Amino acid sequence: PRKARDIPDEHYQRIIETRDAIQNKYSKETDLGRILFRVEGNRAGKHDPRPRVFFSDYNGNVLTTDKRSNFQLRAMQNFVTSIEDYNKPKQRLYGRYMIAGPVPIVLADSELLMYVGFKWNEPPPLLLRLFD
Amino acid sequence: RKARDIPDEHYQRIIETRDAIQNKYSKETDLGRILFRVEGNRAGKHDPRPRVFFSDYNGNVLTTDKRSNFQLRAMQNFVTSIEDYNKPKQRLYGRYMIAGPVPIVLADSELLMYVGFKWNEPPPLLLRLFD
């Protein structure tokens, strides 16, 4: 029963920035596999708190070297197949793992889509009790 | 500048207390009496409880003048900062978050309800550029 929600402007702006950055860093590389390998290489493990970058094509296929966390992979696949409009980036919550995208990206002279997964830690509650 | 979404639990809660306040004072025909009573439950300015604010559909904050001027400034700013009266959002004023508006009916008058509450958690903001 999901909910494609807007990405907060700061988050989206950031995503755009790291997209452009990744694009510029690997502008020399002509091998897509090498790029994906390098990019995903910077994660130290599955419990790595850092935002994880995912990729897909324009045909509904997630592109990744298999990573230690199957859950993030399931969530990403679901997100990719759940997209209603490839021109509007949105975010979806999978348990405690938020996923945002897609944003267009060019790697190895190929047009692909970038996404960002990151665990989302449920805000401290406010109450606001019935007894006024 | 940062009109952010209200977390679903928070928004759901806000809706619940809105409906609750609506049902509690359904008998009352005096708006001033309602506002007075509602705001009466706060014990002081340092009261940690979420503070309920009100406004009309003409940009005016409705409240009996209170102990905390800061919350009042923040609320006024929020009300005049609203881009769309049909989408509730939240804005951070220092450490004081303000969420709204949500429609409410008090004394057969259509008004808007807001909730202010101090926010003690600037992160989670973890991100990176080593990629």
Image (cartoon, coloured by chain):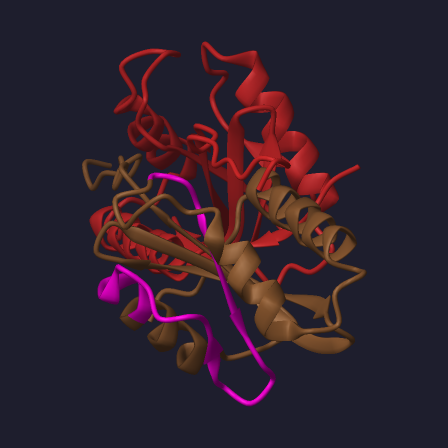
Chain colours: A red, B brown
For the record, the magenta segment spans B48-72
Q: Residue at x 68, y 73 (%)?
A: B30
Horizontal and vertical percent for residue A4? 66, 50
Of the 4 image quadrants, the one containing the C terminus of chain B is top left
User: Vertically, is B42 above or below B128?
Assistant: below
Question: Can residue B101 be seen in the rendering of this structure?
Answer: no
Is residue A49 placed above or below B18 in the rendered structure? above
Q: Position of residue A42 (x, y in %)?
A: 25, 24
**Residue at x 64% of width, y 37% of height:** A130
Magenta highlight on residue A8? no
For the residue pair B109 and B5, the one nearer the viewer reads as B109
Q: Residue at x 27, y 60 (%)?
A: B67
Q: Is residue A72 left or right of residue B95?
A: right
Residue located farthest toward the bottom when viewing the structure as drawn:
B58
- Whether residue A94 appears in this view of the structure is yes
Q: Residue A110 appears at what percent x and percent y?
A: 47, 53
Q: Residue at x 41, y 40 (%)?
A: B49
Residue A33: x and y in percent read: 42, 32
In the image, residue A58 above or below residue B65: above
Residue situated in front as seen by the camera: A31 or B51: B51
Q: Quadrant of residue B116?
A: bottom left
